[PDB]
Length: 346
Image (cartoon, rainbow, N blue to C red):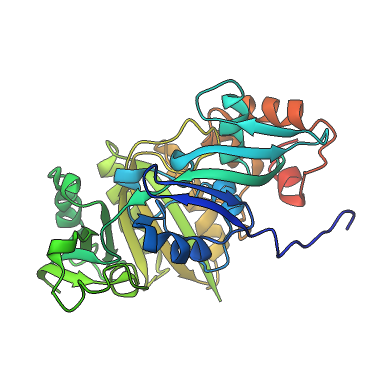
């Protein structure tokens, strides 16, 4: 396995300044660790994780996104600088708009194939409390769910997501339980909670914390461009027809994207389904991949893919630009993984 080092002590938080919302941090720092440390400073990690073990270096590498993408974008959006260890042993200082910005944005896209992220400066989101104030809504059909996200009311909530019915036959199909909200201001909390503001179906202005608001299978996530709404509906309908019933289904409308060539999010309709591993599933997924790509969509790529190199290269129009950068920074493919070879990133 060649070079294998484990550095659990590379998790130092160097500085937290609430006046700049800036945090100077080791790449080994977990986002969970970061928020516990940044909370008393009135700072909030700009894109929430999905694991208490995911690191800053990993969050930049995967360019993670959450329920607030339409307002905050992706995690790469908030990186002000980082130190990259490259194949030649050099430690590069990368900024999103200075020279080396090409390497910067190739780093945000890539999963460490551009080198090892060692340290980073991240701009935090200022907050008065650790609570959300939210509105709950329910729709009766897929068409209603679409219309609900098309009134331009997304500008009134920094966070937004929906759970839709993917099992029911139309017109029930696509009916959703929608949850939208924002960070609570101090004056919006009940007095019971104002003492320690930064402590770790249908409704209006409900105050809830992080674990109340944000809360054998095949994870499948895709995004279809906003204008292709009829094509998006078609995919949802055909999924329901296929017989592959998913219980947990997340719906979301992405905002604009990064300058990162391999950044997943594009503006449009984001759907996360958990397919029970039935017979003929892999055939349907293949038949689901071509449909998504056909309309100009994109798939999410984890280790659980099950995604060909042709599909991957087709998803990302700037992939050749990225590959050129990877080669210039790692010609012998020292950081190259098995995943990189299969997707043909060398």
